[PDB]
Image (tube, helix red, strand yellow):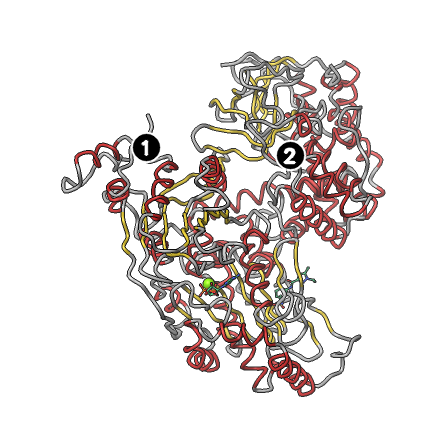
Amino acid sequence: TVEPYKVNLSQDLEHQLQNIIQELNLEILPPPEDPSVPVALNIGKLPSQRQNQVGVVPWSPPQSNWNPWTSSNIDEGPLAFATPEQISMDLKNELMYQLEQDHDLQAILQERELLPVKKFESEILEAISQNSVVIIRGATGCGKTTQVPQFILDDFIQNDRAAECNIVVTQPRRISAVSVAERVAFERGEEPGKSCGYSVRFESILPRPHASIMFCTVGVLLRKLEAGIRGISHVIVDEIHERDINTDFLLVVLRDVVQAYPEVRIVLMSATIDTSMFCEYFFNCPIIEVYGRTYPVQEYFLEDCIQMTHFVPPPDANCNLICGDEYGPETRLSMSQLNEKETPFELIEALLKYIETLNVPGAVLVFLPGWNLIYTMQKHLEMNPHFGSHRYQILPLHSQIPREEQRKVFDPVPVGVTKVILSTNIAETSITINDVVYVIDSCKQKVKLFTAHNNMTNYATVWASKTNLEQRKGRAGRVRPGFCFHLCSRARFERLETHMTPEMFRTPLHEIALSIKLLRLGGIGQFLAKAIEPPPLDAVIEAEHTLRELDALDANDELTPLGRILAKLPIEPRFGKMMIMGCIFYVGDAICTIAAATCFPEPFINEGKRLGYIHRNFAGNRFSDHVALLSVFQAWDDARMGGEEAEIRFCEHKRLNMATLRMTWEAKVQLKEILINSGFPEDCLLTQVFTNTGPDNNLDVVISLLAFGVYPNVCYHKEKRKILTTEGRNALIHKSSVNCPFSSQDMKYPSPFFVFGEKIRTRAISAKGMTLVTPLQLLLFASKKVQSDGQIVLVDDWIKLQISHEAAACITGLRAAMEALVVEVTKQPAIISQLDPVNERMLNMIRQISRPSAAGINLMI
Ligand SMILES: Nc1ncnc2c1ncn2[C@@H]1O[C@H](COP(=O)(O)OP(=O)(O)O)[C@@H](O)[C@H]1O
Ligand SMILES: CCn1nc(C(=O)Nc2cccc(NS(C)(=O)=O)c2)cc1C
Ligand SMILES: [Mg+2]
């Protein structure tokens, strides 16, 4: 229930808009006969592709003249025209001397031989040599991840077959691929570069071309499969029990490879779960069990956690209201006062003080869901002097901090000092800490539930499974009889699911859909039906629909020249098309910069409620987080000119996370590299200088293209922090955003329209990373449906605009004209440098309506 926002654009512009759509051969659809029935201004996009069938990804064993990682030959170098025998012998002789000379490596080998998996080495190597596929089931902390790959390599080194061994290991997470590669490197007295290289998204330290272990993510591997798995002996799919969507999709591919090429060796590695599902899938492959030192863990629940602490809190069916009558009268009362949706931060402090009163030295492992709640818990404790450097050592563990800090969890602490690890679900199965005796469990999980109908990326904190709680408890009993503190009532444990819902059921498939087509694996639905647990129908339909809109797929659901580029780009297909459109407007670098910076957390550091002057000053008068992001990036790139220390002193002074800006940059260069290879010229991807205050037409175009990329994320500002969503529901501007004002203040915007990055609903709807746009930019790129009565126009059944019917039908025309050019450009990206004279004015007219002045707006007020 809002007024129609008027648009005071010049008559000069209206002529120019009408002039070009006439030249483009696009008639304006006339006003309706009566205003009660509106007519849509939406123009349908302006070929018969051959039907695909069943096809398996090809395989070939390791060679002596082939580098499997670079996927090319070895003409130059010492291992160029070497014999398989010369190599295998040299690689052994190299290892023989290293094991005798280095005494600090002998000390490391002596630790490797104590790990439970060691005694099974004989069985594992035998199982793999005989059977194509094998499952290596076993408890977390036995060393199946770190050792099994080495055993397989050493078995080929020591037996003089080292030239016939190249191992691929597929970790589900990003940090796990690096962490393990850096660990397995140290365990051979080397650095990653030599024998144990890695390759994650926008970061890779490739191994040597023979007798090597590549620790990559599944997504990285799938993108490099265009050719096929050429020059690889073993494929170790690690942490299958996590049920990562890409892991599940990979197992569908590998099953086809085992069937057609039974010489290859797959090695699935699972935790203590029901592996019968995977076993059956891979033709009842052997399940090599792995066990060792275990300890009985005395697990407690919220009833017991208030019983032995005498705790009292501050001022579906709620399970805290239920309580055993056997438990104390006050215990039952204290618990019922506590909310279930918020994790009890005060109770955790009381449990750390109970651990003290036992007088049994050991480290504490606190399982929280998000960094937001880990950063919360860390503050709470360090505010209390009792938890000081002399007495306590608190260490945060999540996949978004320096690897230096992630390694400090393993470092033994001074005697008397307690080590409390505020970790995520990373320390559940993927990695094991050795010092842990006591374990506190929130019994919560941070899952990315994406609904398509309203584009809601809800990071909901939902309850964990019985399998989660069972394996979180397991971490306690590795050193001694530990204690596990579950922060959920004995009633709530009953109303938990046996297992978690696999990602395959509750994730979008449009990224996997492209991969299927790119790898020529046939039909999207046809393939995904063969998955160990196929995805829901509606998710496949959604994915297929989502891709046909982008023109990534045709009517026959075959890969278009456009879609092929999107499949080769490791980003959201929509942000992939945005980048291509950037290359046409010669702002490709600026757009690549933005696209990249969505793969890492905002480089801005939090220092209170809202950002200070220094952080806001990057935003300028554009009222855009994305322009602030380019502004810091431009200012940071100039701070690198004066060497490495000048870079750090800038980052320090400006309160920026240097680690991010470098990873964001390295990503941008790789995004550029793929567009170049796809055909796009160098001249449209040059680091063009701009200003975030003065009139800049190139920056106007970047905000326009940005509106395209984030759609359907767009909102209307009413007052203060309150904004209206697409569905017509109220929402809050994120406290992080520059457009967020000070507590109870009036921010005066020259336009109420804002496209944004993430739509989050933790409690209420919060719009993060926002960018101001004009009514013209809204109609052009940030809207699909546009109806008109003659005076008013309706944009996706919300936001009414009192604007000329013609101008609206012209702007909606430019979109369809632009859409058509994207198709023509993707057939041959070279044509960007010499576009049609008619099409060069079409882009100039988009550049025109992109300007603030085009909607009668002046930012310098
Ligand atoms: N970075 C590391 N620092 C110290 N110990 C480590 C590290 N990585 C692994 N370990 C040790 O290796 C053993 C288990 O290794 P891992 O391969 O992660 O086990 P699994 O995959 O079977 O759970 C444990 O003793 C653990 O402490
Ligand atoms: C070209 C340099 N480069 N290489 C990689 C990479 O990770 N390659 C890789 C990964 C896993 C397996 C294989 N081999 S395969 C497909 O199974 O044949 C190859 C990343 C970068 C930048
Ligand atoms: Mg593991």
Q: Give the mark toward the camera: 2 or 1.
A: 1
Mark 1 close to ligand 1, CB under 8 Å:
no
> Which element carries disc 2, helix, strand or loop?
helix
Q: Is residue 430 left or right of residue 705?
A: left
Q: Nearer the viewer, residue 188 or 717?
A: 188
What residue is rendered at 55% in x and 11% in y?
3
Which quadrant of the figure contains the C terminus? top right
Q: For mark 2, what is the residue?
A: 708
Q: Is residue 311 above or below residue 544?
A: above
Query: In the rendered picture of this protein, how many numbered marks are placed on residues?
Result: 2
Instruction: Determine whether the beta carbon of the residue marked 2 sits less than 8 angstroms from the nearest atom of ligand 2.
Output: no
Residue 339 numbered tag: 1
* Secondary structure of residue under mark 1: loop
Q: Amino acid at mark 2?
A: Phe
In-front residue for pair 250/601: 601
Q: Is residue 670 above or below residue 90?
A: above
What residue do we see at 49% from left, 72% from top?
111
| Residue 427 visible (yes or no) | yes
Spatial CA span between label 2 and label 1: 41 Å
- Location of residue 643 in the rendering, given as x and y in whole percent from the top left corner: 80, 47
Q: Label 1: few (<14), some or many (≥20) within 10 Å?
A: some
**The quarter of the displayed image where residue 825 is located:** top right
Q: Position of residue 751 (x, y in %)?
A: 65, 18
Q: Residue furthest left?
A: 326
* Of the image marks 2 and 1, the number of the one nearer the N terminus: 1
| Dot 2 and dot 1 residues touching (CB under 8 Å) | no
Residue at position x 43%, y 30% in the image: 763
